[PDB]
Amino acid sequence: AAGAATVLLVIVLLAGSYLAVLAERGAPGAQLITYPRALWWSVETATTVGYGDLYPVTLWGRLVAVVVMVAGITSFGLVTAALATWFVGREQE
Amino acid sequence: AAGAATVLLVIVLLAGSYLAVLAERGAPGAQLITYPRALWWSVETATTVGYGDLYPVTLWGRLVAVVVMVAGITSFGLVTAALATWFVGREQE
Amino acid sequence: VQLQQPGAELVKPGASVKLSCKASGYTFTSDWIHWVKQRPGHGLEWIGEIIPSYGRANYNEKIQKKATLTADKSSSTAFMQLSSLTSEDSAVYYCARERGDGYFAVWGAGTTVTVSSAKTTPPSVYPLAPGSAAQTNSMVTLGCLVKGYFPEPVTVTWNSGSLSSGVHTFPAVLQSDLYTLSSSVTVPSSSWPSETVTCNVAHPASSTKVDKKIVPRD
Amino acid sequence: VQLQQPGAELVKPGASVKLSCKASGYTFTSDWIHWVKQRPGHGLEWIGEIIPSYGRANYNEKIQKKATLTADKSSSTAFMQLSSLTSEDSAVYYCARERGDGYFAVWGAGTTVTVSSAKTTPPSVYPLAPGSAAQTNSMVTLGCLVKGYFPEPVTVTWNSGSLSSGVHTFPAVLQSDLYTLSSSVTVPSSSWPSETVTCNVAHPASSTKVDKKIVPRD
Amino acid sequence: DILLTQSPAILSVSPGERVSFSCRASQSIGTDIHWYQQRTNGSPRLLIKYASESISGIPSRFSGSGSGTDFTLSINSVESEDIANYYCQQSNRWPFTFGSGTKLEI
Amino acid sequence: DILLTQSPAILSVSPGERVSFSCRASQSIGTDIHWYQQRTNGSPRLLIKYASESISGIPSRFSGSGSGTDFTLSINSVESEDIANYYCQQSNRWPFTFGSGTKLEIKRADAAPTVSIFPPSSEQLTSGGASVVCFLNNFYPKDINVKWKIDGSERQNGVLNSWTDQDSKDSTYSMSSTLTLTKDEYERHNSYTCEATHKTSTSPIVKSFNRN
Ligand SMILES: [Ba+2]
Ligand SMILES: [K+]
């Protein structure tokens, strides 16, 4: 609701960032391997952007990626709803 | 509805993955040619992400791709709706 | 045997030929069947794939497209039609079963195609037992001689494969449109002739297999 | 000392060995522990990482995978098991603590592994004071001689480190399965023997450290 | 058509000793390389798949290394039964290609 | 495996003067390179992280430059305490790799060796041996020609030399020379000398001692 679907997105993005490094380390070639840029990747994913910076290459890496999209795109399909209603009515009055 | 628009997305993603390999094999250069990564591509497509990993190059390949976007983006424009309502009310109570 | 294909074929120059590949085991909806060609002493030349279920085939861009692929969905056998051949088109021809994930897990034994106008001759096996006065070392060497066959190849076996230790089958030689090779084997002089030793020579191209025991000189 | 690992080990060829790395300081959920190997006079060969909390380990693709990593989440100590060794597998072995952001902030001191069948001998320290008639320059040079130890290494110190100015410890030499080195120091001839000067020789492999004061010739 | 290039052409070695055939692709293919062993008179036979993973029923001497454009089959020790031609075959972009081949001498 | 290539292998320079080790990656890695200093006998030690940023507790002489495939460690001035091997280690794609290494030499003013001759300790003879040690300390360049003599005559055997890597207080070299014999043999000679012909000294520097 208010700042609720917000919080779940944050749990998803941290754990997603975390699990990606665990899943991607060990596969030769992957650049999704340090906790910083792994987090930026999970934003890049939870939010449709597709910049082509980082992406997974292992199987378990893509699975962690799917978990983010669903749990993200849904959260963000609700977080921007809140922002919309909020500031639009705010500026109305 | 409940877990219904879910199922259609899965039919779309499997068949889409399947037909892509059939359509893309034979064109020199395409990397969309093995049933595994063909499936990951169809997620990558049904869900706006645009990571730049795989994409089609034949004409029939792009057509299979369009079928996924429509049948996907619509399914996923409904699958995340379910998830949203579900867990948000769940956590409300 | 998983992938199964015939032994050898003979084509007149300019004529056509079909080639088979029957696959016991699974016959998945999603399986593909490939064909690879191996000219003697060369690499592996990929020719083309075919998905037998759905029916589509894709051939090699670069090569002279002499071939066309087919299948039999209710027999689990796939075919390849080579049309109008030269002797540049003589090689081994394998088939391979690719699961759809991009490697050739299972291979056939390979078919040996020989494009020539010479005729088909069966082989002439002769035994090769030692002389009547050759001092018997602990091991004893003895073989048989397969002479005058066309076309290649011939499978040579010893006691039908039961004795496969100490065997060297030699390359064939060519002479006036007929081949010739020899095979060898080594047994303990204790265990022969007190055990019997025979050499079997299958020749797929003529559909003739012939046995010959290597007795002493009676 | 942040990362802490033992001094030196001796393995018979073909035998195994474990290696430790106990880390005081923080022990983060997200920390990784790596190991790097340094054959004498060579680069830094990365072997493999391990996240001690979650438990997973990843080894080096290219090298002969002789090793296997472990940890102790309620002791803050990590281990590496090297199995079946040769003398190609003798080197220094560091551990490193990578925060998760991709560099080795903290390093251990390094363990010296020596794969041989020769036996372990402690060292024999002898003092090295000048002759009874050597004109005393302003500074005076004097050392001690560590002879006949196996295996490497030995830590040499002077007055237990309090005097660390003018010191050169020399490389060891090998001879009939025993080593030998020497160390040097220089003090003002005013301040000696009116101040006392001792050399301490720790030898980790045998667990023997030995002191020796460098008196004049009494 | 992707160019797979196996150098060297032939490989001498003494028994029981590590050996590494190299392969090198004309561009980046990731990990989609696969190794096949083919002896005299015999059909080829998969060894390492997807450049690192192993096949069930293959001697553990065979070690799959490499990624990108550099690739390495490796045999941790050698014995006389390994004398054969070795091929690599990419699957990253159509069509599947093969290497030149590399024979192993002792 | 990403290939890091440090050229050149070795680096001469005179004190107080800028120096730049180059590193070059087999492909683009961005800024995910890191530099480590490792001296003789010591463990490595981070210097520059993420190719430009500095570590807290590092002399400000060290300047992190570069991006892409070209990378440069740089020392705005040099002093003798910097003599070490230097490594780069990428973190952009699995697995983390390392460079070949680059060692840093210093051209300095030539200096003559301090010679010291040492008779075998009283303790050492009591077992069954006597070794004469001779220290050549703090010379430059590292090319020095030691020489033993027993009673004026030259002994070519049972000698063990040892050269230190270039020291990192002064940029000078040092060398030892054990003289292995037996106690029995030590007793039936009287004198032992130690001659060192070095670049600075056409006249060879000599030191000796007599038991009697
Ligand atoms: Ba989008
Ligand atoms: K994109």
Image: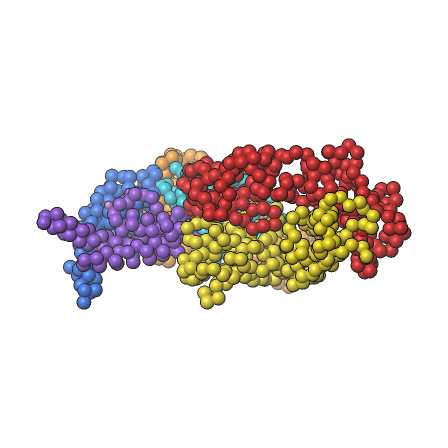
Chain colours: A purple, B blue, C orange, D yellow, E cyan, F red
- Screen quadrant of the N terminus of chain B: bottom left
Query: Residue E19: percent from the left, percent from the top?
Result: 56, 48
- Number of marks drawn: 0
Q: Is residue B27 left or right of residue F70?
A: left
Q: Is residue F173 above or below residue C23?
A: above
Residue B45 showing in the rendered view: no
- Screen quadrant of the C terminus of chain B: bottom left
At x 45%, y 60%, the residue is D26
Q: Is residue E42 left or right of residue C81?
A: right
Of residues C196 and B65, which is closer to you in this image?
Answer: B65
At x 35%, y 44%, the residue is C49
Of residues F4 and F185, which is closer to you in this image?
Answer: F185
Of residues E54 and C155, which is closer to you in this image?
Answer: E54
Q: Quick check: which quadrant has ligand 2?
A: top left
Of residues D29 and D166, which is closer to you in this image?
Answer: D166
At x 83%, y 54%, the residue is F182
At x 29%, y 48%, the residue is A44
Q: Is residue C83 above or below residue E48?
A: above
Q: Is residue F46 above or below residue B80?
A: above
In this view, the residue farthest toward the left is A93
Q: Is residue A77 left or right of residue F36?
A: left
